[PDB]
Image: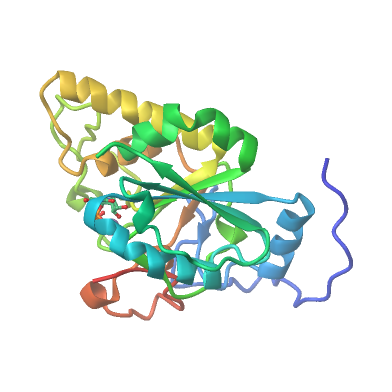
Length: 276
Ligand SMILES: O=c1ccn([C@@H]2O[C@H](COP(=O)(O)OP(=O)(O)O)[C@@H](O)[C@H]2O)c(=O)[nH]1
Ligand SMILES: [Mn+2]
């Protein structure tokens, strides 16, 4: 059950003035594409706080990648879901190298030791029961990243993918999908909506487990068939999101590399970015 929103004073949405005219803000299957200017964060924060939403964030930090954790967590504290309950799940081969990062109230961190792309398996079968019990949504990201601006409840939905920053302007034939019919991740040149980046996807616990289960199974089939998809987990993610349309798509504001790609006019904010 969802209670009434309180009285709120904000600018009237205007039907005969689009928010953004420069970009596609809804997919052909009617999923919002999330850009700055498309959402009133006060309205969304109210909706999700009234549901006492808890967001789990998974991150893998194996071998040398433990070095990225301090900046990743410190900036997540500044920018990720502030005001909401957050549970970070850090998967690592070096529990003692996880930095002591100070967390705001309502936020917690769990270190999960793993053996010394396997992310799909670890998210899916091993952590299944726990996630269902502890969080409402799961967000799965790369660790070699930092938050630079707001990343909030505007992203939450049963299933989301993020536009890869190198391909958002590209034709589908240019997308680096797996192109060999022998792979489970195969997508032909006349198919594809977008090229989604493996570094930022998520949704409800149920939908994320479905996705990671499906991708883990497809990867296993490929392995048994002696084939490895061109872009590994990302290739399989793209195949999944082709056949199971996401209910929101995040713009490249949500996964950017300023060193590689600069700061184009179309991006009003750079929210979550590669660390060189
Ligand atoms: O030795 C490694 C390699 C990869 N990773 C994890 O898996 C992601 C692997 O992708 P990587 O960032 O190296 O390449 P990219 O996705 O940027 O092309 C990293 O963010 C880490 O979270 C890791 O922890 N240790
Ligand atoms: Mn990365």
